[PDB]
Image (cartoon, coloured by chain):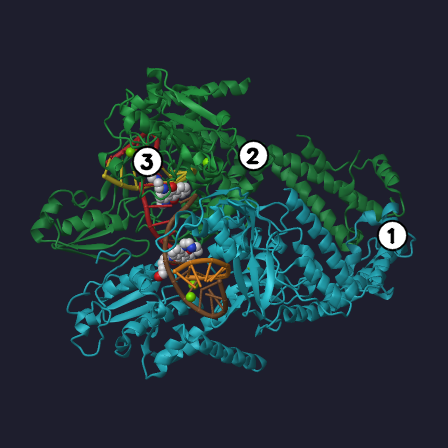
Chain colours: A cyan, B green, C orange, D red, E yellow, F brown
Amino acid sequence: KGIPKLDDANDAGGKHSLECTLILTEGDSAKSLAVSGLGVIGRDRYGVFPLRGKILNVREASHKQIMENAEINNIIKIVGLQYKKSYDDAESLKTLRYGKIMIMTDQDQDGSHIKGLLINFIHHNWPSLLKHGFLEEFITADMERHRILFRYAGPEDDAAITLAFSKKKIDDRKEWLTNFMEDRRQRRLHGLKHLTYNDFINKELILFSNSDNERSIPSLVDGFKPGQRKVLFTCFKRNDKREVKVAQLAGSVAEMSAYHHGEQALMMTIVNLAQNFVGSNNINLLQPIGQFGTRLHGGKDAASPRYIFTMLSTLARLLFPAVDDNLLKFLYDDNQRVEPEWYIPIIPMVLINGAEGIGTGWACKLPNYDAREIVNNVRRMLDGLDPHPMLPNYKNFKGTIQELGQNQYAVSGEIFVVDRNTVEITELPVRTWTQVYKEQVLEPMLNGTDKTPALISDYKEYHTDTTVKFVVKMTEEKLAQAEAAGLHKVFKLQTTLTCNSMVLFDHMGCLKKYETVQDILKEFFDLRLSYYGLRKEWLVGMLGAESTKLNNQARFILEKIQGKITIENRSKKDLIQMLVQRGYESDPVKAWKEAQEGPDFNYILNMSLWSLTKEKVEELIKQRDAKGREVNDLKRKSPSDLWKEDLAAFVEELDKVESQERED
Amino acid sequence: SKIKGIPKLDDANDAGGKHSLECTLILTEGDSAKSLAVSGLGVIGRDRYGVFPLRGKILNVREASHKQIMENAEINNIIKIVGLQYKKSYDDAESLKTLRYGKIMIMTDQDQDGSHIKGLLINFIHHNWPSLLKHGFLEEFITPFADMERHRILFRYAGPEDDAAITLAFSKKKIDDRKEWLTNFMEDRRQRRLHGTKHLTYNDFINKELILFSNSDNERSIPSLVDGFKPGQRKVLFTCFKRNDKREVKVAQLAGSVAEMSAYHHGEQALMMTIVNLAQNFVGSNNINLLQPIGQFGTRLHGGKDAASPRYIFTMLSTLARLLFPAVDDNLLKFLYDDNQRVEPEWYIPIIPMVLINGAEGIGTGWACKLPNYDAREIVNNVRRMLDGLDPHPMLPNYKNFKGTIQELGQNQYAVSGEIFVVDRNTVEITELPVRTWTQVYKEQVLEPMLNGPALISDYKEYHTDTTVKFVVKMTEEKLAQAEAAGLHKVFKLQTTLTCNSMVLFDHMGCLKKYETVQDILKEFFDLRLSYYGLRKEWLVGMLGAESTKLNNQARFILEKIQGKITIENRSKKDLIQMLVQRGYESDPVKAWKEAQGPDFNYILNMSLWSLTKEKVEELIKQRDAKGREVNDLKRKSPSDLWKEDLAAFVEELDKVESQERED
DNA sequence: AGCCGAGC
DNA sequence: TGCAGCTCGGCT
DNA sequence: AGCCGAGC
DNA sequence: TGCAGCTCGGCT
Ligand SMILES: O=C1c2ccccc2C(=O)c2c(NCCNCCO)ccc(NCCNCCO)c21
Ligand SMILES: O=C1c2ccccc2C(=O)c2c(NCCNCCO)ccc(NCCNCCO)c21
Ligand SMILES: [Mg+2]
Ligand SMILES: [Mg+2]
Ligand SMILES: [Mg+2]
Ligand SMILES: [Mg+2]
Ligand SMILES: [Mg+2]
Ligand SMILES: [Mg+2]
């Protein structure tokens, strides 16, 4: 007692304790449905207590963490659990205020994950309790066919719980999930009350684990996770010419693209897409209009999403050309068409902004690469040559990145000895934030700590919001020692960067590990090249259909102004039959679109009466002719040519955009 | 002396030292402004300048309970940071020895709500330490920084007229004087409208700055007589109409939509709450909810306080909305502008006085407004009666689905009773609570005390539903007879009084007025709405007239084309435009009519070629005649006839909608 | 130990 | 995801 | 000793 | 308006 949000059971703590159920709900809303579902009657045997958000994995959480956790302590107090005390006999169980815990989560994967973390919590502290049948679940009277009993049934349950939640079973989880993904491919080519913990883990929780990967680990093809892809898709559909509140953009994405989660995560994703400070995006697809955070705090200083604004970068449709949309496979969420399975950008975006995310079994980490360097390599491969090797590269980073080994790099800031008493620091290594360096490095150097001596006499700061300048004073003696020991080393201006986890989803939807970024580059290249061929086939078909369509329209207009044909007072039916008999083609553009998965002459008869006038007749001829020349000008271009055009246009604008950024 | 457990404070380096009285504490409006002051001070400023942010409006300490004052976080925080002590005169220069800061600089938004926070801060210091105002303790920083001194206004205390100004603004004893104060302001501004420093005194801040807030408080809090809306509410409707959603929208998303579309200059949470309020339909809320509660919008159980978050509930227009606010009337409204953007009208003009239906209520400065709900059908019937020149029946308050009783004690005085019935000589039954008594509150504040304590009842059970109230109460046969001896409704507090002597509203001209009876409100509404039916008729005769002319010309052209009487084939634009003039075709009749508060033939020449076909020629002729009849039919009707048509349509959909509610 | 970020 | 309190006037 | 609601 | 912590993996 004395715990808020708890609706303790009436008979709890008394002689009916072991016949009392604590209902633990995912969220306050689920709690209040449990409350109205009990009525007056249920309050004797049933208590209810909400949890907000994911809970601690206690199995390898530190002791400070476990002792300080609100939720876990609240559950312990409410139920009467005691650490170390096993529940073997029946005199033990007389110490509990409740006899059962009934977990009521959303019937979604994240719901399953909470069920799992709760199960994990009991199993790790009181495994004996699991055997007595302590845990139940409420799936969403009928109210008894909704209840399911978790059954312990031997040591294959201890193995399954540990497979999901032990820091020592990461490799096991990879195998586990590899088997799962392999099975579900096989099932895709063909077709399609007690619950053991093993069956829960291996038939329900694994769906969360998989979904966690699908949402946290990006695609090779466009560098996007599904949430980020929804943000772009929504922005492309909107086509905003002026900025939008981020919070408002989030609701739009939720609605236009069937995003089924809390909008806060969306707003945060949008902020992460727009950020443009040293160590975030080499090319932000979204414009950071307002305070989106700075290198002073790693963006942690962004303003609230209801006071910041964004819109597409002019580089966005240059990187993801609208016409290629006709080539994408757009997904469906209950009969609404949403974002595509991936976009197909002109260079590999996954390398530019350096994908990163954490799933189950695997994680992704990729550093940034230089956009012009990637353009040049793509041009090289278009020439049949081999791509040059690429080092990680961060836009506006003044330091150095040197190869140390396979997928390992030294990232160094800049420190120059000015006089015998003064060093100057003008760059921090990538992802070292200014405030953090000040507090964790320079302060301890000025003040000493309990464990370290002072090393400097003073420091002064001269940063701008995008640059770094520390002026540090020392004694001639201490500077001399610092040099001998290595300035970057002493000043923590040198960090390593290790990339042995380049895990991405390939274009088929398969999770692969890539050993080098040249492998990533080459797989991207082969795919993008074939999509340029698909674009050509599509444009020839479409432009050809438009040519035909203009020819028929222009022929009618001429046949009309010469008295060769009349529609005046002719009936619909006779007009159609006259047109057929004179070899006018049914809507060619519609016919073409149709052949991509009664005769229609509306493209002709929907023309305005203006069409018959002198200038409009001339203008219609010039357009008919111009389309013909446009069909042919396209046929003369190779997929390589089309690509090289896109790349040239992109670089022109990239130069202009980066130039305006250095002035502003 | 330092300061410890005040996390958001940036203390001046020299604060609390010998150089205390040269230190300045900057109080900001919100954390946002706190960070801009922190940057503005840089590293230099951190010595003499302190920064502490206040979130929200602060306590009015003049006439506040002793408890409120002691428990309030901001006031107590300011006191610790500055080192003030209650009941100490800061008259000499020795008394100032105990302050950690010598002055406070207030930094707020330069809007009316900022002025209010300034005033409340001034009120705080003034009421506790007048002494300090003489020494010039308070200053302010005007804002849209290294040019600080031009931005820095000092407050001057010049005499007991400064005391009177502050007291007039913030004393519970000077409500009447505030009425007079604002009446002058509204009058002077009505006159000016027809026709055409460094050391601010308190009197001038109050009478030239704060009064601007007090007035804005009224403009946003007191409803209009015409449509019963406040500006926030009006903007929400205007947006809904403009949007015309055919399916539900998330409340949070609609709020963002309103802000964008109607230039709503405030936080969106307030707007989300307003939206929820507009949509509620439980007993005691709206009689006709103009927005639909799709999701959990609160219940009579908690007075709606149990509504879900605005991001998990949906809304759209009631089918009754455009029946009450007919679209055609939009053409008669004066729409407002917010700097090159057309926004909501100054009012909508509904077909019955909505201000009576859902019972307007708000609190301003000097004035407040309360109005109870009235029955929709009774109002329709009084409108009909007045249309027939009869007398309007007097009206009693009516709450949709209220099962109890509302009795008139006298003008604007009513007694509202719930329902209590004797079941047996041991048992009573409560089946209705008085209007605006919420179920959980009644249980907690009435029944519980009666069960516990000198205890009057022996037990009680609950059989509520979401929308109905049922308590069964068990009593001792002696106690019941006693309870029944006094009033049963009295003992069980099932009778409340409702008193309506503050029916203050903005009239159609924008003047604030106190109405004595609803009959007065009804008359004034009535004279204005009848007059707008006149306008709608004139407007419709004119526009339909233009449309008729437009169709006449179009039909004419078509008939002349299909007969050879006119040809456009291969004619230049000029020759064709000049020809049409010569034949007396009229430049776009509708365009011309609209402009009326070279020739344009596009309305003829933009017609499709289909127009010349048999079926289309007949359809055009039918349409032309249809419009002919429509103009004529309308010309014969009175404004009063039009009004009866709208009312009849409104009542038919009300019967349908309300029927469907009493089944779902 | 704590970052990275898309979920609750 | 939910948590946190004030203004202003009339009324009880 | 607090509701009502549009603001911060 | 801003406040509150946890997962999952790789690597510092
Ligand atoms: O529980 C949540 C939560 C739930 C659903 C959506 C969002 C949140 C949430 O943001 C949150 C907290 N936010 C603080 C800043 N981090 C930004 C990321 O959104 C803080 C605490 C918190 N829950 C507390 C209990 N969890 C502790 C583990 O047992 C939430
Ligand atoms: O300061 C605010 C605040 C500021 C701007 C917008 C909203 C709020 C706000 O909601 C708020 C609180 N919300 C509780 C729910 N009530 C309904 C209104 O949304 C609670 C406290 C609070 N500020 C605390 C300081 N005021 C203390 C007076 O001395 C705010
Ligand atoms: Mg869920
Ligand atoms: Mg990135
Ligand atoms: Mg403001
Ligand atoms: Mg109301
Ligand atoms: Mg009061
Ligand atoms: Mg970890």
Q: Amino acid at mark 3?
A: Ile
Ligand 2 visible in quadrant:
top left
Q: Is residue E2 above or below residue B64?
A: below
The residue to which callout 3 is attached is B81
The residue to which callout 1 is attached is A622
Q: Amino acid at mark 1?
A: Lys
The secondary element bearing badge 1 is classed as helix
Q: Is residue B594 above or below residue B292?
A: above
Task: Answer few, some or many: residues within 10 Å of disc 2's Cα (few below 14, many 20 plus, some between 14 and 19).
Answer: few
Give the distance between the C-alpha atoms of the residues marked 3 and 1, in whole angstroms: 79 Å
Give the residue drawn at x 60%, y 60%.
A401
**Chain where mark 2 sits:** B
Task: Answer few, some or many: residues within 10 Å of disc 3's Cα (few below 14, many 20 plus, some between 14 and 19).
Answer: many
Q: Which mark is residue B338?
A: 2
Residue B369 position in % (x across, y down): 37, 32
Q: Are marks 2 and 1 on the same chain?
A: no
Q: Are marks 3 and 1 in contact (CB under 8 Å)?
A: no
Residue B568 position in % (x across, y down): 87, 45
Q: Are marks 3 and 2 in contact (CB under 8 Å)?
A: no
Ligand 4 is within 8 Å of the C-beta of the residue at disc 1: no
Name the mark nearer the viewer: 3 or 1: 3
Please say whether residue B251 is visible from this viewpoint.
no
Q: Are marks 3 and 2 on the same chain?
A: yes
Q: Nearer the viewer, residue A282 or A15?
A: A282
**Chain where mark 3 sits:** B
The secondary element bearing badge 2 is classed as loop
Give the distance between the C-alpha atoms of the residues marked 3 and 2, in whole angstroms: 41 Å
